[PDB]
Length: 34
Length: 39
Length: 39
Image (cartoon, rainbow over all chains, first blue to last red; front, side, top):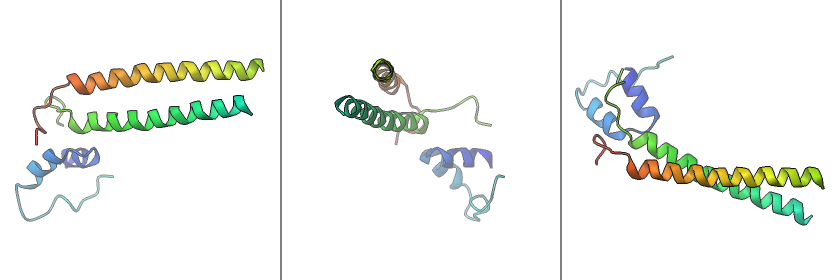
């Protein structure tokens, strides 16, 4: 949750790619942290 | 007028250098690696 | 004239410190190591 927000916030593309490739259900991109 | 124009050019140069510096710092944040505080 | 000259000196000092800061940040980018985002 928090690591994905941090990576997307500061353009860490490698972390986002290696984190969002785990599953194809897409339950992490659609969320709001505060 | 000459002094005011010189001050304006100095401020414009400061602004341009600040844009370049901000871009460099954004690159530093983008490319640096973190292994301890990964939350 | 005195106030304008003081402002000009303050801006000159800001410019010099910004050059030094930009050089330091360029050094940071040059010398930092990246092990995660190597593309």
